[PDB]
Image (cartoon, grey):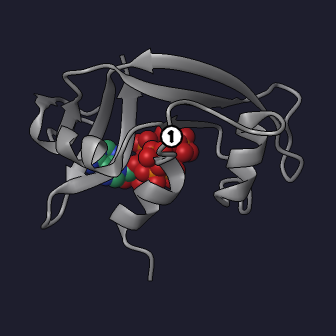
Amino acid sequence: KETAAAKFERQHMDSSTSAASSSNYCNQMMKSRNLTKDRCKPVNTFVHESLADVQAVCSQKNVACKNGQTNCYQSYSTMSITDCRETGSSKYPNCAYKTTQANKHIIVACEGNPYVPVHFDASV
Ligand SMILES: Nc1ncnc2c1ncn2[C@@H]1O[C@H](COP(=O)(O)OP(=O)(O)OP(=O)(O)OP(=O)(O)OP(=O)(O)OP(=O)(O)OP(=O)(O)O)[C@@H](O)[C@H]1O
């Protein structure tokens, strides 16, 4: 079975310098990572950093999670990311996304042993 940690990698890791794609990055990535299979995932962030760099955030700045848990962590450095937001015309199963590239601090929730990211909470 896919662990929460593996799911975080499938949903959010895109190790590279920045978004690269032959067509609309978000439409191709949301499809290829199976984020459009059971619904159109409405918002999603891809992180263009090494897996070690993202995992290291779990020992960086402790912040409250949007859901009130306290196992969220904000990166000290800005990171290269791409946000995918479903369009107003998007309707499952014909999902469609707008692509926003950014350099922002990421906030992830971490869990488990080893303590690793399992949920992407926000970017600031
Ligand atoms: N330590 C944590 N702190 C906060 N939330 C956490 C933590 N661990 C797991 N979660 C889970 O996050 C899921 C979304 O919950 P909530 O956010 O509280 O409700 P929502 O109404 O907002 O859902 P939505 O559909 O609108 O937006 P999602 O697309 O994010 O949902 P889903 O993909 O299924 O979530 P994930 O797998 O984690 O992807 P991702 O890493 O977040 O991208 C939900 O299962 C929570 O239990």
Q: Residue at left 32%, top 21%?
A: 105
The reply, left or right, for residue 29 in relation to residue 60 is: right
Q: Residue at left 30%, top 42%?
A: 54
Location of residue 86 in the rendering, given as x and y in whole percent from the top left corner: 73, 32
Quick one: SS at disc 1?
A: loop
Location of residue 116 in the rendering, given as x and y in whole percent from the top left corner: 22, 55
Residue at the far front in the pictured view: 17
Location of residue 114 in the rendering, given as x and y in whole percent from the top left corner: 14, 65
Q: In which quarter of the image is residue 42?
A: top right
Task: Pick the residue in front: 32 or 109.
Answer: 32
Screen quadrant of the N terminus: bottom left
Three-letter residue code for mark 1: Ser
Screen quadrant of the C terminus: top left
Q: Residue at left 30%, top 39%?
A: 108
* Residue 67 vertical position relative to residue 79 in the rendered view, above or below: below
* Residue 9 vertical position relative to residue 124 in the rendered view, above or below: below
Q: Residue at left 39%, top 18%?
A: 104
Q: In which quarter of the image is residue 70?
A: top left
The reply, left or right, for residue 15 in relation to residue 72 is: right
